[PDB]
Image: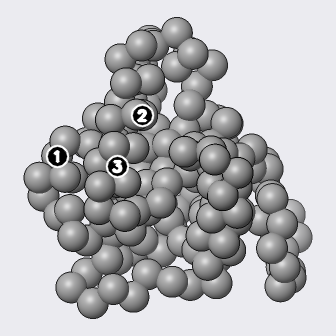
């Protein structure tokens, strides 16, 4: 008989760790809208399905991706496509923390991975709008702002390392 669950808090600032916190909030809501893509190799598919609707892509690079030449090409491939339609993107340094997010409340559908050793996939998500472009929220505004400043430094892609729970 143990019940002390009551956690809360708020702040109103742009900060580096707040970028990946903010991302987790929006993606959870974006599953609730059912208007998003998932999986690194959907690059060609999403370009042929809803290229006008595309708003932002996320990629999560493993330690194992530093040795996967195909998945490295998949990252620069999806980067060519989003740039062609003017769509910003972000590359997270932490495969485990983005894998935590897909367990919390985004991608809460049939997306779990419990086997021997499956290959690196299900490490990307893409946010897209309906026929009325309304994807803002204060969280994704913080993301766009941060990503624009680091992109201004001649980085073709901004990058970050988001916190644990």
Tag 2 secondary structure = helix
Q: Are marks 1 and 2 in contact (CB under 8 Å)?
A: no
Closer to us: 107 or 56: 56
Left or right: 3 as drawn, with respect to 65 = right
* Disc 2 to disc 3, C-alpha distance: 14 Å
Tag 1 secondary structure = helix
Residue displayed at 52% across by 19% down: 65
Quarter-of-image position of residue 63:
top right
Residue displayed at 51% across by 67% down: 28
Q: Earlier in the sequence, mark 1 or mark 2?
A: 1
Q: Which residue is mark 2?
A: 75
In this rendering, the label closer to the viewer, 2 or 3: 2
Quarter-of-image position of residue 107:
bottom left
* Disc 1 to disc 3, C-alpha distance: 11 Å
Quarter of the image with the N terminus in it: bottom right
Closer to us: 102 or 85: 85
Query: Where is residue 83 drawn, in percent x and y?
Result: 37, 54
* Disc 1 to disc 2, C-alpha distance: 14 Å
In this rendering, the label closer to the viewer, 1 or 3: 1
Left or right: 142 as drawn, with respect to 26 = right
Disc marking residue 45: 1
Q: Earlier in the sequence, mark 1 or mark 3?
A: 3
Q: Which residue is mark 3?
A: 38
Residue displayed at 27% across by 43% down: 43
Density class for disc 2 (Cα within 10 Å; few <14, some 14-19, many ≥20) is: some
Say if 131 sits above or below 146 in the image: below
Residue displayed at 77% across by 65% down: 18
Left or right: 105 as drawn, with respect to 109 = right
């Amino acid at each position: 008989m143990t019940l002390e669950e009551f956690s809360a808090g708020e702040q109103k600032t742009e900060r580096m760790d707040k970028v990946g916190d903010a991302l987790e909030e929006v993606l959870s809501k974006a599953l609730s809208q059912r208007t998003i893509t998932v999986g690194v190799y959907e690059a060609a598919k999403l370009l042929n399905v809803d290229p006008d609707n595309v708003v932002l892509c996320l990629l999560a690079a493993d330690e194992d991706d530093d040795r996967d030449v195909a998945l490295q090409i998949h990252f620069t491939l999806i980067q060519a496509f989003c740039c062609e339609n003017d769509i910003n993107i972000l590359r997270v340094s932490n495969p485990g923390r983005l894998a935590e997010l897909l367990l919390l409340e985004t991608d809460a559908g049939p997306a779990a991975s419990e086997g021997a050793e499956q290959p690196p996939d299900l490490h990307c998500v893409l946010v897209t709008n309906p026929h009325s472009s309304q994807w803002k929220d204060p969280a994704l505004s913080q993301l766009i702002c941060f990503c624009r400043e680091s992109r201004y430094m001649d980085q073709w892609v901004p990058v970050i390392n988001l916190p644990e729970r």
